[PDB]
Image (cartoon, coloured by chain):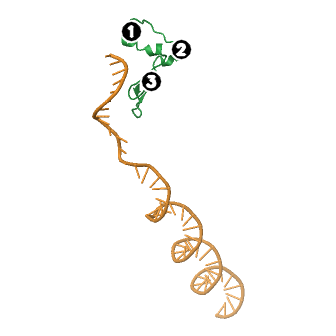
Chain colours: A green, B orange
Amino acid sequence: VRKDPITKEWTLEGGALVLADKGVCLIDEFDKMNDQDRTSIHEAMEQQSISISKAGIV
DNA sequence: TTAAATTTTGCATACGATCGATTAATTTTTGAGTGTGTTTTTTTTTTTTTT
């Protein structure tokens, strides 16, 4: 989520998994990536969905 | 010595040259009337993301 320069409103931004909605996401050097950065993708890799609750946006 | 022909000179007069009085276009102004734009943004605080 991010704040737009026009009207300062909180709007969503698509991540890497949003751009692979019917495709393949590919991770190189998976072990050396941080645990917070490794395993933030549980809901996309299990529920096939991204549930977001931040900045008044669900 | 005296009378007629002739050409000159003064004067009146009519016609053009030129300035002046008047006057009609014109075109610039004449502000008068009318349409219209206008305050003004402002750091401060929250939340998030990366560092």
Tag on residue A16? none
Residue at mark 1 shares a chain with residue at mark 3: yes
For this rendering, which residue is in front, B47 or A29? B47
Q: Residue at x 45, y 9 (%)?
A: A27
Which image quarter is the N terminus of chain A in? top left
- Identity, as a three-letter code, of the amino acid under mark 3: Glu
- Identity, as a three-letter code, of the amino acid under mark 2: Gly
Q: Which residue is mark 2?
A: A23
The chain letter under disc 2 is: A
The spot of residue B11 in percent (x, y) is 58, 86
Mark closer to the chain start, 2 or 3: 3
Q: Measure how far apart labels 1 and 2 are at the Cα level.
A: 22 Å
- Image vertical order of residue B14 relative to residue A6, above or below: below
Q: Residue at x 46, y 22 (%)?
A: A14
Q: Which residue is mark 1?
A: A33
The spot of residue B38 in percent (x, y) is 40, 49
Q: Quadrant of residue B16?
A: bottom right
Dot 3 surroundings within 10 Å: few (below 14), some, or many (20 or more)? few
The chain letter under disc 3 is: A
The spot of residue B50 in percent (x, y) is 36, 18
Q: Residue at x 49, y 12 (%)?
A: A25
- Identity, as a three-letter code, of the amino acid under mark 1: Met
Q: Which residue is mark 3?
A: A13
- Image vertical order of residue B21 relative to residue A32, above or below: below
For this rendering, which residue is in front, B19 or B31? B31
Under circle 1, the secondary element is loop
For this rendering, which residue is in front, A23 or A39? A39
